[PDB]
Image (cartoon, rainbow over all chains, first blue to last red):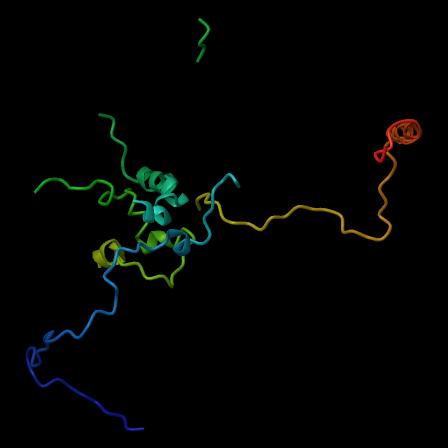
Amino acid sequence: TQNINTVDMGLGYTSNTCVAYVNRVRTDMGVRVQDLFRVFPMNVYRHDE
Amino acid sequence: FVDALKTLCHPVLHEPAPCLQTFTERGPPSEEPMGG
Amino acid sequence: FAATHNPWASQAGCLSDVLYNTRHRERLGYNSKFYSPCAQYFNTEEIIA
Amino acid sequence: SLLHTFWRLPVAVFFEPHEENVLRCPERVLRRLLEDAAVTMRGGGWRED
C-alpha cells in the first residue's frame, strides 16, 4: 500500500476539462419505449380478469 | 401510439389516490329524498 | 412567462409527480434497478437541496 | 399508508386427493334414475342394426 495525500495549491480553479471528441453512441437513440409493468412489477388491477 | 401500450394501460396512471393525497395537503380555498 | 405550459407535469399533485419522483415512487411498489431517464427532472428533494 | 393493490398469490383451500376420499351416492334419487336409464336399454336400439 502507498497512502498519498493531495492538497490543492491554487486559490481558484487551476484545472480545466472540456468535452473534446465523441467516438460513438452507446444507445440506439431510438423510440422503443420502456415498459411500465417491468418497472412496476407489483401493481395489478382490482378486478382479476 | 400503440408501442406505448406498455405505458398507457398501466394501473398506476388510473390511481388518483396519491394525487388526492398530496392534493389534500394544500389549503382548500372557499372562494336526499328524490320522491317529493 | 406564462404560469406553466403543461399542467399534468408541473403541479404538486400532477400525474408525473406521483409517477417519477423517486421519493414518491418508493411509496409505490417499484423496481429501483430500472434507470428512468426523467428522474433528474422530477426528484425535487435533490432540486430543493 | 395508502391502499394500493398488489399481486397476491392465488390461495384457495381444497382437499388433497387420497386413495379413499370417496364420492357418495347422489342422494339415492339419481341412483334410481340411473338404474332406470340402465334397465331401459334392454329394449331399444342396438347401433349395429
